[PDB]
Amino acid sequence: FAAAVGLAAPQXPAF
């Protein structure tokens, strides 16, 4: 599951 977070992670600041 690490990939799930690592790939998403840089988009988080869209919040």
Image (cartoon, rainbow, N blue to C red):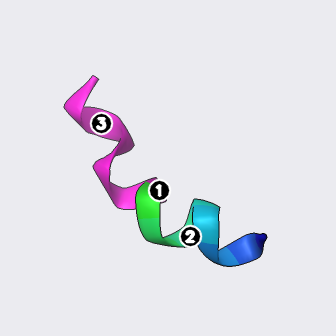
Q: Nearer the viewer, mark 3 or mark 2?
A: 2
Disc 3 to disc 2, C-alpha distance = 14 Å
Instruction: Assess disc 3: are there few (<14), some (14-19) or many (≥20) residues with their C-alpha within 10 Å of its C-alpha.
Output: few
User: For residue 6, which numbered disc appears in the image?
Assistant: 2
| Residue 8 percent location from the top left of the image | 44, 58
Disc 1 to disc 2, C-alpha distance = 5 Å
The image quarter in which residue 15 lies: top left
Q: Amino acid at mark 1?
A: Ala
For residue 6, side relative to residue 9 (left or right): right
User: For residue 1, which numbered disc appears in the image?
Assistant: none
Instruction: Assess disc 2: are there few (<14), some (14-19) or many (≥20) residues with their C-alpha within 10 Å of its C-alpha.
Output: few
Tell me which segment is drawn in magenta: 9-15
The residue indicated by pointer 3 is 13
| Residue 10 percent location from the top left of the image | 35, 58
Q: Residue at x 78, y 70 (%)?
A: 1
| Contact? badges 1 and 2 (CB < 8 Å) | yes
User: For residue 9, which numbered disc appears in the image?
Assistant: 1
* Local secondary structure at mark 1: helix
For residue 15, side relative to residue 5 (left or right): left
